[PDB]
Amino acid sequence: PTAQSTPLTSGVNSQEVPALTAVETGASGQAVPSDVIETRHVVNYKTRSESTLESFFGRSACVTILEVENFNATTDADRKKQFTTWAITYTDTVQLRRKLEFFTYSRFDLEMTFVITERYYASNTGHARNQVYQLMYIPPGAPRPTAWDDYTWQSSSNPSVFYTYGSAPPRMSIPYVGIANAYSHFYDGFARVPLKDETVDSGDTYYGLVTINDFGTLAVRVVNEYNPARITSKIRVYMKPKHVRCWCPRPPRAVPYRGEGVDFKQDSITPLTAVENINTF
Amino acid sequence: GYSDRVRQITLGNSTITTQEAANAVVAYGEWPSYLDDKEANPIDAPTEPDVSSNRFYTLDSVQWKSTSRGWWWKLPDALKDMGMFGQNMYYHYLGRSGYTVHVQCNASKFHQGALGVFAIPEYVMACNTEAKTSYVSYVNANPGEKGGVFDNAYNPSAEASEGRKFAALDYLLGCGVLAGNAFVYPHQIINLRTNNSATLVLPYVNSLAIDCMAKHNNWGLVILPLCKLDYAPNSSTEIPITVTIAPMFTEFNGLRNITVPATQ
Amino acid sequence: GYSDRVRQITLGNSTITTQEAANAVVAYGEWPSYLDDKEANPIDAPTEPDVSSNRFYTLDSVQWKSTSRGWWWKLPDALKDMGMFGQNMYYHYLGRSGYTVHVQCNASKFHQGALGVFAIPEYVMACNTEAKTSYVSYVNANPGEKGGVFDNAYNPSAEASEGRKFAALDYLLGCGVLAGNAFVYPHQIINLRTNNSATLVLPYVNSLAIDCMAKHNNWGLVILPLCKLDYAPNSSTEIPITVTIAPMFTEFNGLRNITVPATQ
Amino acid sequence: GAQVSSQKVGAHVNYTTINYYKDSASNAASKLDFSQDPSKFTEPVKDIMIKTAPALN
Amino acid sequence: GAQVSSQKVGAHVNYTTINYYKDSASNAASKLDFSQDPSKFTEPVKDIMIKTAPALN
Amino acid sequence: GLPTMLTPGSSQFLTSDDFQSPCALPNFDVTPPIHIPGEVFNMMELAEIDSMIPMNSVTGKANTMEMYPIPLDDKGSATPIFSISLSPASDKRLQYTMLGEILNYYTHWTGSLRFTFLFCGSMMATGKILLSYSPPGAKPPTTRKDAMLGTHIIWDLGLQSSCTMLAPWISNTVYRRCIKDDFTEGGYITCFYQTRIVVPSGTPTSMFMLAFVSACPDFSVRLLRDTNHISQRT
Ligand SMILES: [Ca+2]
Ligand SMILES: [Ca+2]
Ligand SMILES: [Ca+2]
Ligand SMILES: [Ca+2]
Ligand SMILES: [Cl-]
Ligand SMILES: [Cl-]
Ligand SMILES: [Cl-]
Ligand SMILES: [Cl-]
Ligand SMILES: [Cl-]
Ligand SMILES: [Cl-]
Ligand SMILES: [Cl-]
Ligand SMILES: [Cl-]
Ligand SMILES: [Cl-]
């Protein structure tokens, strides 16, 4: 299937007036060149292959950067650097989020890929053996780790991936996991109805998707015990929507995001550059 | 004889006429319908109130002035206090509805102006504090039939507690997108030289078969002056805009005692 | 749905719309056409420039005032400097063309006035000296897209050299016949209460199959105010008249170097 | 259970797919779907509008 | 969807190809194309020249 | 060799992977199977079994056998006999039922819940009891006149000892979450005297009923997860 060919047409002198319409109807303009000019025949062999939803979304996009370290931790703050937890979302970054938000609703499977990098913190503390990482998916309700070596990492039921530093970026597929018939990119509502004369506080409650969304937690640790040399790591998380359906198109984000909602920032709401004149080529 | 400009709509005991229409929009080309057994979720026999609730309710009119920046409503919020529709909505945990939206604005052959009338699924709007995100009170999000107005200025509050309302900034459609692109949503235009009414028929739109109407608005209704009202003999003249909405194919599940939402 | 008042005309890359037409005239009931082999004269393979030249060219607008006596153009003279039509005309000894003439004049439901729009074969006009006969300069006969105006007075020159222009006397149609009889020529009327445009489709008209366009105008276009422009709030108001003309079925013979006519 | 399908043409042509996993979520990208109906967004009108006819009669 | 083709001969002979990718751009080298028409460069003349005849008669 | 190219995921250990692996004991002759009674195929078979709700887990009764029996008497109070939220995974009283324990290995649940009540007074005790399920979004019922507007059954005490009240599946979402969550709140179960318990003389004037919960055949769970009900020191 190809984009439209142009038919051979000459002029008209007619009560047929395809050049005029009334967009008050809610219909866009429909006229094509053959309606308003003399056209030659042009066979169009070109296709819209690369603008299908699968093609538009068919890329692994970085959605977050996590940090973990491996060293002899003697304080609470340093113990908390030995592992990290991240609420799974696409809202830490802007590029994939903006593409998804052309649509109100979506349904897709997810390919998740990880890029893991290390550096030495210092040069005077000897060396470090090759590190193994555990990335544990903690679904809502499953116990979250409070230490890098607590019981939760035995991961009897949670999916974990063990990654050996220097090996191919680890990768797994996630089904469509939504509890609705599609994911909502926008939710015009609340998680509960506040009722007349209730004692529950209405002053610090939130609005929209943030009140209802929960895709669980990614927990990451270095499985190795500490070397004399402190190693600091970054874990880049990549998402690719696949087997994609989307509904109800939206205008794309025109101004910077300032969080997980649709809110905008007072110093960043002037996207257009003023032209010198309405007559500027 | 039959004309794109002349239309009658009857639902229940209510009829609308227009002699200066511009066709009618059926959002996404889909007429509303009842929920099929093969797409159903809650298993209790639903209430289908039919003519008691599936009828035209006329909201309080608003005044279009040369200085108006626009108006918004949410659905089903705008109809929550409307006759038996409101009672069925609040006596049930779950509800679904389509709508016929009829926006009315007549003037004269000497007036000029154009209203964009947009039906927006999941019309999420920005909050009015930069101390927080997604920080809107239930009461400010759900104004009912009075709806709200757009502004051409964004003045977020000093204190988080004072900014728990929408920053309904007209040119960003109150949600960080350019208003010029609102035409991707089901719409008509009331251009005073052409037409005096807009008609949008809306199917139920959601990621679910049925949902909590008291928690969740499925549609926003936005009326934006695309071209300002002008009238040479009196630039300060006002003409009413009247919004009349009929629920359609309403279905409710999970009957219990009545929901009475907070008012402060 | 289809109306005598609403028309689209497309030629080449150009389209005209009108929503207040009054049908369209096909002069002498004959659509233009190419020259048949059984009526041909010059034997060289002709140039048929088609869409490059057979398209709407809009002339400079003129202002209709309560005091205007009327306007004239000649064809193909009015189009001699128009894009590729002008180039094809001047690179060839011989040319033939039909035309779509579209005259545009909108006002309001409160204005009144009527323009007679006449297509006149061989529109020969009187000279402005009584010392000579048939004494008109090429430059004054061929004003191009600016055309000329009628007068309600005849003031022939003292000196023959000062009177080498048309005596475009309105009531004698600039040629010694009564203007009231101009309706024997293909015409429409723009009556401001009825219509805002006139459309005339003209076949090639001549005593020859093809002729020297730089020597000879086949058609005159005359616009006469039959009823004066009147507007109660401002009797001195002006409304534009815009003339848009498309050559049709153009055919040229006798290619050589370009003709550059005298300008003084 | 090999699927043989047409490749997307290059400069100048079938390819083979076998699914290795028991979950469809594991599968490679969906096949090109050229489905479209712009009219649900560009012309969502109740009464048919013929381009050559007046939009408002 | 295996293709079996003749190998290029060595010192002293089919081989099998399966395409693994959905894009023809991913494919290995095009098969040997022995097409040629040197005359479009060596003899691009309007009137046929017979070698045994005079070039100019 | 066959030309190959390693893809992302290569060498990872995903704990939910499903691959073949070499056998450490090749050619091993497993003990022949025999029929054993009580084979289980699905954890939802276990979820359909009635287990006792620790409905009276108040101070002094929690973590004793007295946490189970629901106090009844012949005084005909208008106050509710018991009140509990339809939060079968997360509620302090439902989480430790057999159904609650199974739900805490899953993230999502759907379907109808069955509440069966056994009256354990004397044969000479009579009474009518209202059992109600109120889907959420309205004032939680604390009076019989609010409770009776919801899904309810009037239980007449008699020769048939037990009464089943259903919490039919009535939800916005297709699944609820196995956590305390406003968005997937399930509503309110309450119980009132419809008349009162009446006894003749020489009969106990206070007595108990037992409440059981089980899943219906429309019930299913998904998204396996670790439970918060078992842990160890490290
Ligand atoms: Ca084509
Ligand atoms: Ca049209
Ligand atoms: Ca055409
Ligand atoms: Ca030779
Ligand atoms: Cl471990
Ligand atoms: Cl170790
Ligand atoms: Cl500029
Ligand atoms: Cl009012
Ligand atoms: Cl209201
Ligand atoms: Cl309140
Ligand atoms: Cl002009
Ligand atoms: Cl000119
Ligand atoms: Cl000269």
Image (cartoon, coloured by chain):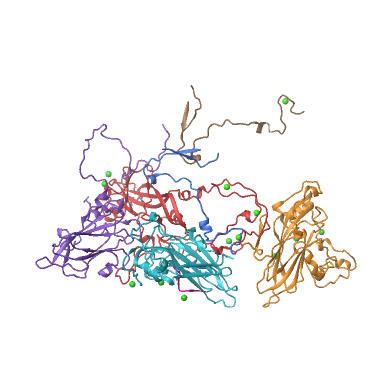
Chain colours: A red, B cyan, C orange, D blue, E brown, F purple
Compared with A159, B106 (above or below) is below
**Frontmost residue, A280 versus F35:** F35
Seen as rendered, the residue at the extreme left is F202
| Residue A56 at x, y percent in the picture | 48, 50
Seen as rendered, the residue at the extreme front is F159
Q: Is residue B153 visible?
A: no
| Residue C214 at x, y percent in the picture | 80, 56
Residue plotted at (75% across, 49% down): C47
| Residue A25 at x, y percent in the picture | 55, 63
Q: Which residues are magenta?
A: B55-64
Please tell me whether residue F187 belongs to the stretch shown in magenta.
Answer: no
Seen as rendered, the residue at the extreme top is E12
Compared with B69, A208 (above or below) is above
Residue plotted at (79% across, 54% down): C259
**Frontmost residue, F153 versus A18:** F153
Query: Quarter of the image holding residue B229?
Result: bottom right
Taking F128 as reference, is F202 left or right? left
| Residue A275 at x, y percent in the picture | 57, 62
Q: Is residue B66 visible?
A: yes
Q: Work out which quarter of the rendered image holds the N terminus of chain C and state it.
A: bottom right
